[PDB]
Structures are given as structure tokens and as C-alpha cells.
Image 1 (cartoon, protein in one colour):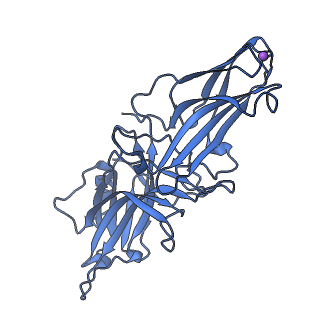
Image 2 (cartoon, helix red, strand yellow; image 1 turned 120 degrees about the vertical axis):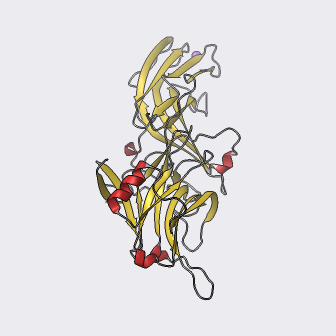
Image 3 (cartoon, helix red, strand yellow; image 1 turned 45 degrees about the horizontal axis):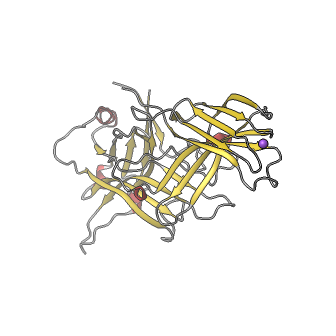
Length: 369
Ligand code: NA
């Protein structure tokens, strides 16, 4: 079985079919959006039909745009002619050949590539506590019909078009970086002896839903007790277009049950799983889609190609493990400050790997249960 997604214009003249809602970037390359457009021959007579792919950044709205009330900067734009048929006939892909075999003679292929310099789907709606507005990067697939008027004004009527917001989803590349690790030491006021914290991760990339084994070694040479060992996954978000908004938020947390007495060491591995489901509040963190939708995830770590300016990504997402130690008799007495350290890591979807029967679903995404 193969689920095909479809949407049809208010006026019934144009119907678009897609194989996926979600298009894979493994960063070596990215999936093209290939699909077909079914037309009503009678409603498209004398008309042209195109499909465009637009990547845009928007600040100030959850979409572009109501009352032109938002800032917008386009990252990429492409458009192909789907009807009348251009040049040679037939599909360039099996999906297309198959969908055309099934749907019949009013169906026409279209294929839209992605380039390698774009970000992946990212959006944020701010929490009450935050300032700065909603923003994100949208990927629009639009199929529309144009016609001519005797006044020589061409027309692109809304009722003849269909707009699908797809996702460009980040999947892991062939290779990952070295084992993440960090070593911090503190010498407190009046003290001759160090508190050391080493922290290590099993690998530099993790998959959404994959448990992250944070291993911690405390060497406490001090007279103090470490009352608490806390471990966080922090999501760090930078808005690099328009407003400068900066967000850092805890998407996962774990507390050890153990303390570290003066003059002792402790080594323990805590396991964290940074999912959006763990978060009651979905606001003020970078997601790959709208809050309302069941399929939405945490944004994957941004990946910038060499030689691309980061502002052109429009929102930067990155992750770190933060380990905070709580030290007895310090705070308000020997420090106004945290004792903590961070180890960065990347978070994305799994590495991808290396006729049929179709079932048609409406493209609109399922709302949150
Ligand atoms: Na001490």
C-alpha cells in the first residue's frame, strides 16, 4: 500500500497529488517534490497551469500573511508549467507514471527540485514569558491556473489554486563528528581544593526519539557536598533574520538520586529523551511544524553548508546537554553563580537507506489528539 496526498481547488478545475507531506534532506542531497496535477479539461481550456515551490521566512505571523502584517524574506523560488503539457510526454519517475496510469488522461507530471543551501522546516510561537513574535520558514507547493483577459490583464484566481505547506525534514548525513565531551573544574572562594565534572556522550548525532546516554563523572575534592546533579537537554534557537530573538529552553530533564559527599567521586549515566511530547508547553521552542498538528516535532539541529551565510537559514537551532551541580553552602554565601557545564550535540532524523496500490488521503494534517 502507498498513501497519496491530494487537494483540489475550490472550483474543482485543479487537483494536486503528492507522494509525501515530508521531504528528506540528508544533506548530501534532498528529495525532489514530484507529483501530478489532474485537470478538468473543460475548466482549463485557454488556461495555463503551473506549480511553484517557494521557501520563505516570515516574522510576525504564523503564516504569510494577514493584512501584509508580517516581515518576509524569500529563500528560494521555482516554478514549472504543468499544463498544457510541455515538450515530451510521459513521467520522469515511477510515482508519476503510476499515478498517471491510475488517474487517467487529464493527469500531468511535475517535478520540483530543492537546492542544497536551504534550511529545513523551523518555526516558533513565543510563550507568554518570551518577547519577540512568531516566525518560521515555510515551504509552499502551489498549483494554480492563469488565464487571459481581453484587456490583456492576466489572472491568477484563488479558487483555481491549491496551496500545500510541505516540510523539509532533516535526516542524518553519512558521517558524524567526534565523541562529545567536556571537562570543567571550579575552585570556590576560600577553598584550596577543586570540584571537577567530566561529561561524555556516546556519539555526536542522535535521532529524534533515540535515548541519549549522558555519562557524568564528578570528582569532589572539596569539603562541600554536591546536593544535586541535574541534566538537561537545552534547545538553543537564534532568529537570524529581522529581529534578533534568542531562545534557550529545556526540552528534557533528569535528576540523579545521588549526592557526592566531600572527598569522593561518582560516575553515573543518565538517559534523556528530548521529545516534544514531554513538553506541556509547546510555545517558545523551535518546532518543525505548527503546534496544532499531531505530526509536528522538535526542529532538528541546523546544518549550514560551507560558504553559506547563516542569516539565510533564517532560524538556527542547536542542542546541548547541560549538567548543573548544586553545591551545599555555596549559593548566597560563596557564589551568586551557577556551577554547570555544557556539551553540544546534534539532533535529527535517522539516516535514510539505499506496480503498486494507491490509497488517497486529503493532504491537510491531523490536529492534535
Ligand atoms: Na572546600
